[PDB]
Amino acid sequence: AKWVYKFEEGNASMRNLLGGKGCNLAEMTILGMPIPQGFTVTTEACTEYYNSGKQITQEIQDQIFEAITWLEELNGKKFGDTEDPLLVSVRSGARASMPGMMDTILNLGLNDVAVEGFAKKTGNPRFAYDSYRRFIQMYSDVVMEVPKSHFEKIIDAMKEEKGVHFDTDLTADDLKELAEKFKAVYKEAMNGEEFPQEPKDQLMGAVKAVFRSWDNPRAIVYRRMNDIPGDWGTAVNVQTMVFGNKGETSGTGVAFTRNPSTGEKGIYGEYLINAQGEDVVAGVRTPQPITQLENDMPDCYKQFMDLAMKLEKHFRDMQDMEFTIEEGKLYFLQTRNGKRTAPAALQIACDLVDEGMITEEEAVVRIEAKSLDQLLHPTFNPAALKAGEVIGSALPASPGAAAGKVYFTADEAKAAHEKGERVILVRLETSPEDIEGMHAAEGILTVRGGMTSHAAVVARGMGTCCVSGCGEIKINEEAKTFELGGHTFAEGDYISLDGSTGKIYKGDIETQEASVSGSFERIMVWADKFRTLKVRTNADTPEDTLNAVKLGAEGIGLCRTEHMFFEADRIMKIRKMILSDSVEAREEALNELIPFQKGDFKAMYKALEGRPMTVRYLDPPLHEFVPHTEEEQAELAKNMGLTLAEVKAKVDELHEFNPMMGHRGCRLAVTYPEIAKMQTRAVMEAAIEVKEETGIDIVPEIMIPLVGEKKELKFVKDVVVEVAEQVKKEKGSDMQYHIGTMIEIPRAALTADAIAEEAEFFSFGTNDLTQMTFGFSRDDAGKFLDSYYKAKIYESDPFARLDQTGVGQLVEMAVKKGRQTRPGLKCGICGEHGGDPSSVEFCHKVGLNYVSCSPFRVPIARLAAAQAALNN
Amino acid sequence: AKWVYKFEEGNASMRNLLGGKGCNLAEMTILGMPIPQGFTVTTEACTEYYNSGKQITQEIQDQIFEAITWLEELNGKKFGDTEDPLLVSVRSGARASMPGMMDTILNLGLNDVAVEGFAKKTGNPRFAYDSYRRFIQMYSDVVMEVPKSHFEKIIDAMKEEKGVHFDTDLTADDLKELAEKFKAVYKEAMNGEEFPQEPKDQLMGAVKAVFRSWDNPRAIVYRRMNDIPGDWGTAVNVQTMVFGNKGETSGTGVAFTRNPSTGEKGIYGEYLINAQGEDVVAGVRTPQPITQLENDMPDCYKQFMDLAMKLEKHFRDMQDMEFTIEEGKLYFLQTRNGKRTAPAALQIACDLVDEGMITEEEAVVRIEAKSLDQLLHPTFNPAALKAGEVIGSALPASPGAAAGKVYFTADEAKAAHEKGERVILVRLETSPEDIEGMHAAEGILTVRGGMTSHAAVVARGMGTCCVSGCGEIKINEEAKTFELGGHTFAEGDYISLDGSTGKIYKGDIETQEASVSGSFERIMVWADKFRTLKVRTNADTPEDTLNAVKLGAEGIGLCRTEHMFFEADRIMKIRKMILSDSVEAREEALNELIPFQKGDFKAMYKALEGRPMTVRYLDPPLHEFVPHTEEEQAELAKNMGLTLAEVKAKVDELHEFNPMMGHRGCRLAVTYPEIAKMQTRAVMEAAIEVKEETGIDIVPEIMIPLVGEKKELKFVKDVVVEVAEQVKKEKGSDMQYHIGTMIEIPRAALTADAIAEEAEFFSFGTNDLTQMTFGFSRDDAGKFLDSYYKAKIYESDPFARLDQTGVGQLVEMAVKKGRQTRPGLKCGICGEHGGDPSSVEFCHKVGLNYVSCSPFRVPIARLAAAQAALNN
Ligand SMILES: [N+]
Ligand SMILES: [N+]
C-alpha cells in the first residue's frame, strides 16, 4: 500500500492515519509556517508491523528510505553522510495526544564518521560532539532501555571531575570523550554489540522501537486510564533537524497560548538558551519563563507570538507549541490543542465564545467531561492553611490541595494507596515508568523540572496537584528520606502541597468541600440548553440530596433503603422479625420500624420539594442483618428469650453459597410480603403528610429490585398497590404513584416487553447487570482483572465503563421491548456507569430518559449528556 | 390643580406622581385585573401640604371627597353610611418602594352606627365587630401613635379570661366588648377626645397622618440608608375594601413569583384563612406556605397562579403580590417588583434572560449595585458549623452567617454596635421603629412572624441574616434574657444564626471568606461588555491585590506606602532620619530603608503580572512617626545617643495645630527631597528587576500627594525624574514611567490645566477633597453630622457618597481643564467614593478613565460602571 506521506500530502482530517502530531505538522506546513520538512510513517504501518509477527515489511522500509531520499534532495545533503550529513528527528504520535508518554530521538544520523563531517561543515566541534552524545543517549534510552541513570552518572562524574558546573561548560574535547563513554555504556549493555553506525539501521531501529513501545506495559495501562483503544496504533514522524544547541543565539522552548492550569489568556511556558528540548523538560538549568525571551531575543519573540496567535486562530483553541531557534531563526516543531485542567477548560471555552471565536455548541463539545471531577476536589480549609507550617515552595505546576504520606518510588506509592493511604510521590523528576504511582497519588512533588516537566504535564492531565522544581529538597532514595527546611522526612510522613501557590507544608493540612466558578455555571447553562437526557442523583439522605440539587440534579434515581434497617436504632426490629416463627410476629416486629422509616422519608420529601425520587425496596438477603459475632448473637438471644444455640441455628439457616444470587430482593418480598407492605406504608404515609404540610405535590416512585419474570413483579406490585390504596383511603388522599423495577437480571431485559406490562418505569441497575452478564462478582474479580488488563483481554474496567458491546445489548433491548408494550415507559440508569461519560452517551443514544449518578458526579453527567445530544 | 386620580386615569409611567403603589394599582386596572376600585391623592398633594404650613388645602380635600363620591356611585353605597356602608383602605406609597415602612389602615368608615348597619347587611355581626376593633386599632396606631402593646394586652386579657386560644375564637359579643375597650384606649390617650365617628374626619385624619409621617425621624433615617430624596413626598391610595376575615372561605396572602432569598423560580410566600393582612405579618397564627392554598382552595389557587404569571410577564420581573380572597372570590390588592437579596437578583436576572423575557442590558440595569456587598459577607466555616451546638431552628427569612452578642431593643443593639460589638437583635417581632438597630445588627432573630413578617422583609432588603418565628424562644424583656432549648441567654451572650437553614447556635461560630456564583460571573461578563470605565483597586499588599484581581480588578489605583515606614522593622530608620540634623544623616538613615521597601515593591509587581499600580508617595506629617510615649521616646533617645529631653523637644517641634493641613505630602518632599528620592529608587529598582526576571513589562505610576500648585508638583517631579533616570542608567533599562498627582486640595482642581502641564495622570483623592471643600474633618464631624441628618440639612453622608452638587463641581472642572492642556490625561478616583454606585456613575459621566475601590467592593464598581454606561 502507501505507508508514508510527506507533510505536504496531509492535513488535520487525516488524523487517524497520520496521528495527531503528523496531521498537525501537515496542517502547519499547509499554512506555510517555518516547519522543517519531513514525513510520516502511518498508523496503518504500525498495524501492518503487528500483523507481520512484529516486523517491518520490505515494502514499508522501501518507502521510508524512499522518503529519506526525498528529504536529501530538498536539503542537498545525504542522510548521515560521512561528509556533510543530514540528521533527523524521529518522533512517535497516535491519533490521540498522550503528553509525557511518547518518544523523541534527536540527531539521528550521527556516527563515528558523520560527526567529524558535521563538525567541519558547521565549523563547530563542540556542537557536533554535544549533538552526538545526546543522540547516543536518547537512542540507548528509547530503542533499548538503558536508564538515563547510567548516562547522567557519567556526565556528572566528568563535570564534577573537571570542576565545571554546567553541561554547557564542557569542551569539544570532553564531549568526544563523553560520547565514547556513552557508546561504551550501550555496548556494556548490548551483550557486546556496538552502537549502530549505519544511518539506515538507526532509522529502522528507532521506527521499530516506536511500534514495539505501543505494547509496553506502561502504554497499555496509561491507555486504559485515558480510554484509548489499542488498535489505533501510532505513527512515526521523521523530520530534518533544527538545533537550539548551536550557540548563544540558539534555543528551544515549549509554550501554551493560554495558561493550562487556570485558563487565563496569555502566553505561558518556558525555554532555555543553547539547549535541546530534553534540557528544558529536565530543569537542571532553571528554565526561563517564556515571557522573558522578549528580553533576550525581541525579534524572534515578536515572530513567535504572531505565529502563536495565528495557530490558536486557525485551530480555534488554546495551543501547546514547541519551537526551536537556530542561530536567530525561528522554527515551529509541533502544535496541538493543549491539555488542561477542568477550571482552565471552562475559562478558556468561555473566553473563546465571548471573543466570537467559537460557538456555545463548540465550547460544550470540546471540554473533557471526565475532567470535571476536579472541580469537586476538596480545597484546603483557609484557616488551617494560614496556621500551617510552610517548609518550602516551588512551581505551582498543577493545581489542587494534596495531603498525604510520602513515598519515593511510583511502586511504593501505589502499593501504599492500595492499602488505603493518601500518598504523596516525591521524586527527583518523574518518567513514563512512574505513571501508575502518579495516578495513585494525591499529589506530586519534585526536585527538578518546570511547568513543562514530565510531572507537570502528566499531572495537569490527571487533574492532580503538583509542585515542581523544589531545589531545596534533598532526597536520599536508599534511606527513603528527604530533607527540606527545618527537617528530614521519612517514608510515610505527612506533607501537604498547594498546587496553586507552590507552597509545601509539614503535616496533613485540613481540607474542606470546594465551591464553583461562573464559567462552570455558564458552561452548565449552555449544556442544559442542548441536553435532552435529564440527570438525577443517587442519594440516600437529605444532605446528599441538597448537594446534588445544588450541582444541577433534577431529582433522585436511586434512594437505597438498607440503612433504614441497619441503623443502631433499627437493626433490632429486623433482627426480631428474622428470628420470629409467625407471619404475625414478623408483621408486629416490622411495624415497629414504621415510625422510623416514615421519618426518614418525610425528611427526604421535605428536602426534595417536589422533585421525584425512585425508592428501591429492600435489596440484600436476611443474613446481612443477623449478627455474625458469637457475642452479638448472644446479646440477641438474650433480648429475645432464645438460647445462643437457637440464634446460631437461624443464622446458619440463612447462610448462602452465593449471596449475590440467593434469597433477596423481589424473591424475599414474595416469601415475606410483610416487608414490602411496611416499606409501602412508610413511603406513602410520609409522602401524603409532606404533601399536606406543603401543598407541594409528590408522585412516589417505588422500585422493586432483582426481578426476572413478569408474574414475579406482579405478585409484589399487587401487595404494594393494596397497601398504597389503603393508606390513601385512611388519609383521604388521591396521590398518584408509580411502581417500577430495576433491570438488573439478564432475564428482565430479555423479557422486558412482558415486564413492562406491570412495570411503570425501568431503572437499569448496571452494576449487577454487568456482574450477571459477565458472570463475575466485582469483589472477587480483582484476582484476574489485572492480569486481563495487562494481557489486553479487556481495555476498560466493566464496572466503571458500560460494556457497550455486550451489556449494552441488554440495556438497548430492554428499552426497545419495554416500549413495545408501554410506549411512554420511563427508563433510567443508576449503576456507577450513570456518572461515566461514554456510558451516558450510550444511554442517550438508546433512548433512556435520564441518568443518575452520585451527587459529586452530577456536573460530569450533565455535560456528558449535552455532548451526547450534540454528537448524535 | 388636579390632586386626585382614579386608578383608571393612571399608568406605570406616572410613578413620580402616583407613587409606585398607585401606578401599579393603575396598571393592573388597565390590565382588567380583579382590583377593587379606588383613587390616588398624588405626591404633589404631599408637597402642597408641606407648602401650606402642614395642612390640607381646601381644594385638595374637596377633590378627595369628590372621588369618594365617585366611589360611592360605583358601589351603590355611601361612605361610612349608618345603614349599608362603603368602607375603604387607605395606604401610603412613594415613588420608591420602602417595604416594611409605609402605612395601611383597613376598614376606614366604621363607627358606632355604621358597624350595626354593616352587621345587618352582611348578616354577620362577628365579622362586623371584628372589622371595627381592627380599624380602631390600626387608626390609633397609624394616625396617633398609641402602641399595639396597649391593644394586644387587652385582646390577650380577654381571650385568656375567656379561656379561648385564638383571636378567631371571639364571639360577636366579645368583639363589641373589645372595640369599646379599644375606643377607651384611644380616648385614654387623646386627652379625653373620642375616636372620630365621622367617616370624613377619619379619612382626612388618615390622609394627614400619611403626609405627616413622611417627616417622622424613622422615615428620615431609613431614606438616608436607602438613598431616597425627601422632596419626593408620598402619595395616598384609597380603595374600596375586600375582606379576608369574612369567614372560612376567605383569606389573605402575600407571595413572590420567585424566591427573594435564593432567586429560585416558583411561587413563594404565605397566607391565612379568615384574616386580614395584619394577621399574616404578625404570625400569632402560624402562616401557611403559599403552595398549601392549592390544597384548601384549588380553584382560587389556579386563578391566582395564572394572574401571578401574567403579572411577572407584563412587568417583565419577579413580582411581590398581595391578594385577598373574599368568600371564594379572588382579589389582587398590590404588585411591585419584589425586593430581593443579591444572589436572588443575579439568579433571577439570569433566568429571565435565558427564558427570553429580558435582554442582557435589562438584566444589568435592574440589579441594585450596592447590594452586591452581600456576596462577600463571610459564610460559616463548615467544620465549625457541624461542630456547633444547635439550640433551636425556625424560618430562614433572610440568608447569611450572623454571629454576635444579643440585645433586646433596637437602641441597645445600635449603641452596642457603635462601641464596636457584633450584635444580634432578638425580639418578639420588629417594627419601623427598630430600623436603626436592625441596620446595626449582624443578624436578626424573632419569636413570631414568617417570610413576610416585618423582620423578614426589611432584612432581605438590607441583605442581613434573619431567622424568624422561633416560637421555642422565651424573651424576658425586663430582665433582658431569653430561654431557648438548653438554657437562658443574657444580654451580651454570643449566639449565631444561619439565615439559609434557619438554625440557631450557642456561641460565636467561626466564619470564613465567601466564594462566588456563576450567575455572578455571568452578570459580570455582561457588565464588562457594557462598561467603559476600567476598575482598579485600593490595595497595599500582595494578598489584597490577588483578592481584587480575582473579583475583576484590572490593577491598582492606590497603593499607600505609609506601612513601609511604620512597620516594626522600618520605624527606627525613619525615626532616625527625623531626629537627625544633617541632610547627609537624613539620607543615610533613609537609605537603610531601601532594601526593605524595594522588597515590598517587588512582591507587589510579582503579584501584579503587568497590571498598573498607582504608588502614592509619603502622605502624613513627621509627627506621625515619632514616639508619643515618654517610654518609647526614652528608648529612642537611648538608641540614638540623645537625652530624653532632646527627643521630646523634636517631638514637640513637629507637633501641629491641624495635622490635616500641616507640613506633609508634597510640602514634605519639598523640604526633604531625600524622602522622594528614596521612594523612587525603591520603586524603580523593584520594577526593573521584576521586569528582568519575568520579561513582563511594567510602567510605574508615581503619584505625589497633596499638591495645590503647578511649580510645587514640578519641584518634586524633577527630583523623582532625576533619580528614576539614574536608576535606569545604572541598570541599563529603558523602562517607561509616569509621574502624576492626587487632586485632593481644591486649588489643584481650580488650576488643573496648569497642574496638567507637569502631571501625567490625576487621581481624585475625594476623601480629602471632600474634607477641604466642606471644611470639616471626618473624625470630628460626628458631633454634628447626626444632628444634620435628623434636621434633613444633609440627606447623605458626604464621606460615603460623592457630593455631586459641590465637590462634584471640582472633580468635573479638574478633568475638563486638565484635558485642555493634556488631552490624553488619564483620570481616576480612589477616595471611598470609588466603591459607591452613584459616585461611580458621576465619574463615568464626567469622563474619568477608571475608578478604584477596596478589593471586596470591586464587583459593586464593575456593575455600577456598566450601569452608568447604559444609563447615559
Ligand atoms: N441488586
Ligand atoms: N491626603
Image: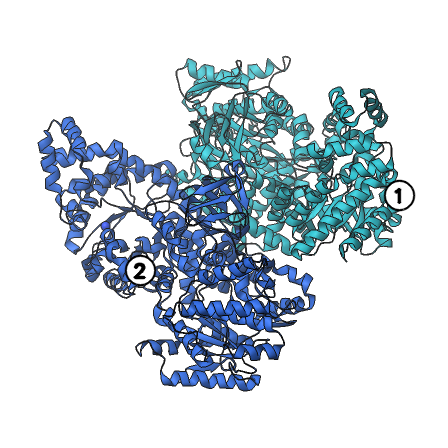
Chain colours: A cyan, B blue
Residue B485 falls left or right of residue A752: left
Task: Spot the residue most to the right.
Answer: A711
Q: Nearer the viewer, mark 1 or mark 2?
A: 1
Q: Dot 2 corresponds to which residue?
A: B802
Corner quadrant of residue A615 = top right
Q: Nearer the viewer, residue B99 or B182?
A: B182
Tell me where residue B32 appears, x and y as whole percent. 59, 78
Q: Nearer the viewer, residue B596 or A60?
A: B596
> Is mark 1 in CB contact (under 8 Å) with mark 2?
no
Tell me where residue B60 appears, x and y as whole percent. 39, 83
Residue at point 34%, 50% (across, down): B415
Tell me the number on the disc at residue A712. 1
* Classed neighbour count for the residue bearing mark 2: other residues with Cα under 10 Å, few (<14), some (14–19), many (≥20): many
Up/down of A22 relative to B801, above or below: above
Q: Amino acid at mark 1?
A: Glu
Residue B354 falls left or right of residue B191: right
Residue at point 13%, 38% (across, down): B651
Q: Is mark 2 within 8 Å of ligand 2?
A: no
Residue B48 falls left or right of residue B465: left
* Residue B589 at least partly seen: yes
State how far apart marks 1 and 2 are (Cα).
78 Å
Q: Amino acid at mark 2?
A: Leu
Q: Nearer the viewer, residue B853 or B488?
A: B488
* Classed neighbour count for the residue bearing mark 1: other residues with Cα under 10 Å, few (<14), some (14–19), many (≥20): some
Q: Secondary structure at mark 1?
A: helix
Tell me where residue A719 appears, x and y as whole percent. 85, 46
Up/down of A297 relative to B258, above or below: above
Q: Secondary structure at mark 2?
A: loop
